[PDB]
Image: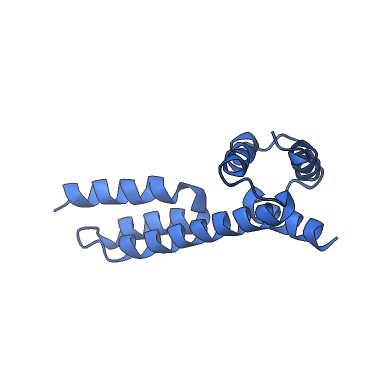
Length: 93
Length: 38
């Protein structure tokens, strides 16, 4: 459509706040820097979830699959899914 | 607010609305890199 992306404000907000802290001399160069590192952090954070869930010992095969399936489909809630998979795992001990 | 920050973030914002990329962060790396190259 032509909509306003959810999270656009928060995402722009955080770049600005970090601009404050370091006062980079070139806003463009820092943006390339900020968002690259913000990307890498997310890839890093997602990779890790996948595995942990991978070998969580008290999950049956069907649960591990559901969580991993949700994880591959939606990186943004990797923290949400890792939490839910650990809660359901701890209870299943 | 440092000078230029508003115009810079506005520019990115218009293109986000123009193009509706599926990931804002990934597009950000895309958008600002092209801007740096120019």
